[PDB]
Image (cartoon, rainbow, N blue to C red; front, side, top):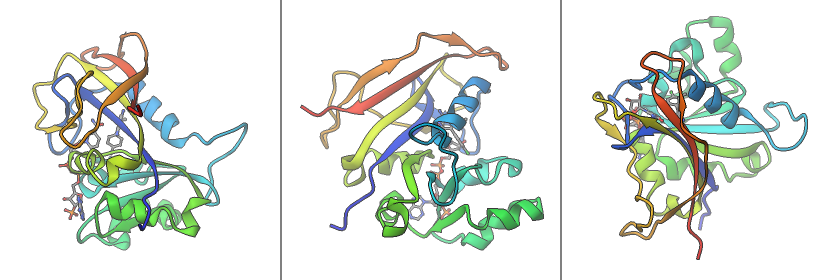
Length: 219
Ligand SMILES: NC(=O)C1=CN([C@@H]2O[C@H](COP(=O)(O)OP(=O)(O)OC[C@H]3O[C@@H](n4cnc5c(N)ncnc54)[C@H](OP(=O)(O)O)[C@@H]3O)[C@@H](O)[C@H]2O)C=CC1
Ligand SMILES: CCc1nc(N)nc(N)c1-c1ccc(Cl)cc1
């Protein structure tokens, strides 16, 4: 009251909950990159192609948007919602180097002067409940923290986590989630719905990874 649009988290973290060094993701796992793209891009049902009339949204902090290599700004086929206390939509667009692509990106980027909560209230609007199918929170550290506590955590439907091993020695930013069998002080307990068997990445270092899905426990 007002309600918050339900959402899912997509993240890649190691055993220490490390997700980044403050500016970028330390490891290179191309299989996770591809999976992230498909998971956040894919729409429900058969043969539904993303468009302004219906697509998914990815919500991220301004630093995560900046971490995006300019050539991938904005994330294609998805509404990009950037949280920033100052950066305007125009200022976000100005960071897109290809001027033609920038002209096209005008309808794919939205700047929110607020946190995840503000984004979730906005994504409930008559204009987004129909045009936005699924809302994915994609980072970073500060946004994940907001995602895991009230009032956001209350509408959290799932966490698509890519488990990375071995632990990185460059992570200073984390994704703090209660271990299996534990419930956070606020009351959040996560249950593993599924997890792939460990696989070795073709990227540098050959990091081992698993695609795991977690959902809040609903006794
Ligand atoms: N492994 C993974 O899956 C992921 C890793 N990352 C990594 O994490 C790091 C970035 O994390 P982090 O430092 O926490 O930065 P964030 O991505 O979380 O962005 C923080 C910023 O977002 C905006 N913001 C956050 N809360 C609010 C609010 N309540 N109101 C208005 N604006 C808000 C502000 O930007 P502003 O300064 O403009 O005001 C703030 O500085 C990088 O190392 C990146 O590579 C990021 C996503 C996923
Ligand atoms: C492909 C990396 C990746 N993998 C997973 N599992 N989750 C994420 N949230 C991201 C990610 C991090 C930063 C940006 Cl800028 C875009 C996406």
